[PDB]
Image (spheres, coloured by chain):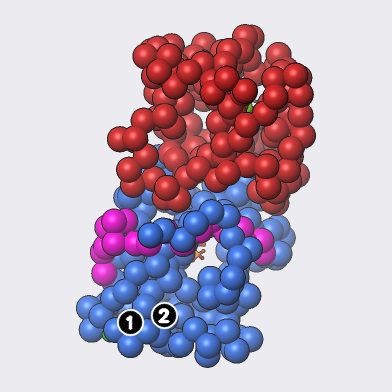
Chain colours: A red, B blue
Amino acid sequence: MMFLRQEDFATVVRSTPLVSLDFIVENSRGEFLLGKRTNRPAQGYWFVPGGRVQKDETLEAAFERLTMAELGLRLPITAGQFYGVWQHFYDDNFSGTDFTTHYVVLGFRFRVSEEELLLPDEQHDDYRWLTSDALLASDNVHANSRAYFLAEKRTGVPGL
Amino acid sequence: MMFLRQEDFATVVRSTPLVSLDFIVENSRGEFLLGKRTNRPAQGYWFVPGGRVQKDETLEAAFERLTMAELGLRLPITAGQFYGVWQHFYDDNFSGTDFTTHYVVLGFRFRVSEEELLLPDEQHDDYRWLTSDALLASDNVHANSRAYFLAEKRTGVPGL
Ligand SMILES: Nc1nc2c(ncn2[C@@H]2O[C@H](COP(=O)(O)OP(=O)(O)O)[C@@H](O)[C@H]2O)c(=O)[nH]1
Ligand SMILES: Nc1nc2c(ncn2[C@@H]2O[C@H](COP(=O)(O)OP(=O)(O)O)[C@@H](O)[C@H]2O)c(=O)[nH]1
Ligand SMILES: [Cl-]
Ligand SMILES: [Mg+2]
Ligand SMILES: [Mg+2]
């Protein structure tokens, strides 16, 4: 557990990869959860929910913290199916356009009931449940979220 | 690609997880490579070779840089069998005992010919090739290296 003050978060983002968990969440209709991001990077794009692991935080603890923060429902890591190690590179950062952000991302897939989520408004100003076909066809869904649904992008992803 | 100044590496290690690749390296007789570490963390322990991924460095590029740096032989990531995601927590760091180090680690296994390595002396002052049974019985092999030969404090799948 360590949420960093902004100065040290800036130095971290400038200097090293972030490590994060992305949640590929399915409902009862075979559709997947995307939120319209309010923060950089990938600001304004539809994206799966996800976030970074903190210093000295286990993956197990991060999964609980992040599902609760992103989805409004605390789930244990055993609820998730590990879905590979991905790499996301952005030209901007949480607080500006002056340096890049790099994430190494652990994907997890799971199915939920919509009524058990309490979707928060901090990181997204709208949410939708999209079919694979629809999300792949939309250039407003960021490429790094579309990639989870493309066979060609899964090739050579460690863990798949 | 970004090798950090010590000042920046210290801020990074204090503040966030490192992401690294560890190499489970087999020879033609089924033994595995361990080096006797000269740097913190895990200083003085026998450990598999491995190291961290830098800012804006792909896993593919890191794998080539790190195999060359650790083994003296450059191999592509396609040569490696993904061997799980692991989490390693140390009470010390490269610079001393003032803060902890946290790694999220991707394991990769592959076989080499001993005669094709050029084992470097920067990070290890000796190297041995041990059977799985032998290294598991040796307490001078760090617990975090022994874990690759059991069992699972492991996230995800061995490839294949
Ligand atoms: N100051 C500060 N902000 C953080 C830290 N970690 C994440 N954030 C920010 O908190 C918000 C949510 O974090 P997260 O879901 O991990 O980021 P995401 O990659 O933008 O979805 C974003 O605006 C992040 O930039 C941190 O340790 N310190
Ligand atoms: N100054 C500096 N040292 C680094 C950096 N990355 C790794 N090191 C050090 O370089 C050496 C080899 O790095 P690596 O194999 O990644 O780390 P290991 O976990 O100690 O095997 C170790 O002494 C590390 O502490 C960095 O960006 N800057
Ligand atoms: Cl050999
Ligand atoms: Mg997030
Ligand atoms: Mg190393």
Which of B118/B97 is in front? Answer: B118
Reading the image, the residue beneath label 2 is B33
Give above or below for B114 relative to B22: below
Magenta-colored span:
B73-90
Q: Is residue B86 left or right of residue A116?
A: left
Nearer mark to the viewer, of 1 and 2:
1
Reading the image, the residue beneath label 1 is B27
Which of A129/A145 is in front? Answer: A129
Badge 1 residue CB within 8 Å of ligand 3 = yes
**SS for dot 2:** strand
The N terminus of chain A is located in which quarter?
top right
Q: Residue B46 appears at what percent x and percent y? A: 53, 81
Instruction: Tell me whether the residue at label 1 lies in contact with that at label 2, contact meaning CB atoms closer than 8 angstroms.
Output: yes
Indicate the chain on which mark 2 is placed.
Answer: B
Q: 10 Å neighbourhood of mark 1: few (<14), some, or many (≥20)?
A: some
**Tag 2: residue type?**
Leu
Q: Number of numbered discs present?
A: 2
What distance separates the C-alpha of mark 1 from that of mark 2? 8 Å
**Tag 1: residue type?**
Asn
Give above or below for B26 relative to B9: below
Q: Is residue B5 left or right of residue B103?
A: left
Q: Residue at x 63, y 75 (%)?
A: B143
Q: Is residue A150 magenta?
A: no
**SS for dot 1:** loop
Give the mark nearest the N terminus, 1 or 2: 1
The label shown at residue B75 is none
Q: Is residue B148 left or right of residue A123?
A: left
| Residue B76 placement: quadrant | bottom left
Badge 2 residue CB within 8 Å of ligand 3 = no
Which of B84/A7 is in front? Answer: B84
